[PDB]
Amino acid sequence: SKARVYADVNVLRPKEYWDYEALTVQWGEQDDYEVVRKVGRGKYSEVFEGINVNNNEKCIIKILKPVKKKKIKREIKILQNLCGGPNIVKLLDIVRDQHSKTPSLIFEYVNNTDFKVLYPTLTDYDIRYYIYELLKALDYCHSQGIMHRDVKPHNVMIDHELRKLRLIDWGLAEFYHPGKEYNVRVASRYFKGPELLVDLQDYDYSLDMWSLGCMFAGMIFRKEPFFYGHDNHDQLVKIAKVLGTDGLNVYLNKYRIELDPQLEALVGRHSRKPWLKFMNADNQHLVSPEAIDFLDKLLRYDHQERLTALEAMTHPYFQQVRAAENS
Ligand SMILES: O=C(O)Cn1cnc2c(Br)c(Br)c(Br)c(Br)c21
Image (cartoon, rainbow, N blue to C red):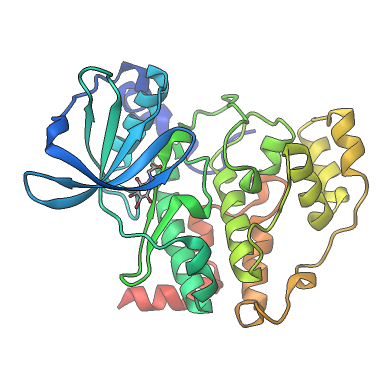
């Protein structure tokens, strides 16, 4: 398998663009940044609102938990390469503690609202608008030879008062090289594409479009998360019960993949459910043939058949967002 767009971005660029192991980190001054309050945490970092003591401007300080040199360089290089792109979080400095060597990444501040409380209040137009803004970020990173590989609501910061969005946490992101076999232990379970779940390692930017489609399904159907598996096997089952097993077998045969027999046994046999099986009273104002059409074109087993992010931006579901942007 090869990406159908942007396959040659790293082939054409200087080796230094993508050879992140050759990066020499240029450390700033740790005392320029002071922690104000904790705002997030995860397996690989704790996140704080901070202040730059020189100019009294807010920032975000991401303090990294113990990590290999290779992995920190990958995230720094990808952030450096993407800084300035539409709706991409901006890495401003990189510092570390002298005694422990604990590194902190310093970002422009973003004033986010908890998605679990925000999404119930978004109107149909707001869903179209924020998904468009997220697609700007995905088409940009893909155009720069990068897959994010962890798109989920937790990594999409939205300041709803200011209608501003940033795609954050580039810690799982990778450069795309044609034919490379990648680790499938990426993304959050509920957003993992079928490629990860069936061990197709030569995947590409289209992985991010499956994760996007799971986010979008969750928003328009008001079902968080949309595919609610308890482990990676159960995740494929939850997908197969919606998309049907016929499509799955076609996919598996095309890429000459066989399922582990236990996984095969769990998946069983399922007809394709129609997307309208999911509409109900709470979500009804958000669900339309344009939304379903757009969703159906993202949630395909075959990663080669999904819309690209640039194709998604042009889908008529977004016509009003485009028209508004034009003036
Ligand atoms: O995980 C990350 O990269 C950083 N991270 C975690 N929670 C984060 C929040 Br809340 C904001 Br606002 C920003 Br900006 C980043 Br950057 C965050």
